[PDB]
Length: 168
Ligand SMILES: Nc1nc2c(ncn2[C@@H]2O[C@H](COP(=O)(O)OP(=O)(O)O)[C@@H](O)[C@H]2O)c(=O)[nH]1
Ligand SMILES: [Mg+2]
Image (cartoon, rainbow, N blue to C red; front, side, top):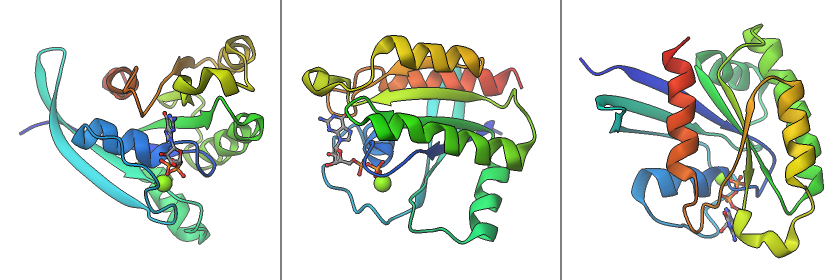
């Protein structure tokens, strides 16, 4: 039987959670994907020679019922905490999600990657690579910049996260 890995996408609105999920899943950039939809996706992928299945839960703010949210988080094995390099407030918001995840999983070593998305909009960058890295260092997690549009580092973030999961 193939090993199953559960990944959870978290972050504020419009940072690219759905766009990253769909690029990785179906290899296509889907613009204006319905913002209030939360859904799960699964498929087989090859990680370092081994065939495994990845399950991705794409969350949305609309679903704010505590019991439901906490259940989704407790079921996740790794998290991609996404923000938009073009929105300073989304970067600041990452602290909020980090707090909720730590509250529910009580594990400061839980597989977690800080993801700065929309790297293709460099000319609108409001968050420098320096400040993002400093924060990542403080939480002892790695930082990766992606673009759901050009697909830069998209496979890398999911793959790197699965590797951390594989080691815990
Ligand atoms: N240029 C650019 N736009 C992006 C990127 N990722 C998402 N977007 C756009 O940002 C908007 C919000 O994306 P969405 O995936 O719905 O964000 P979510 O609310 O986090 O699920 C959509 O209009 C996307 O087409 C990216 O990497 N580059
Ligand atoms: Mg979405």
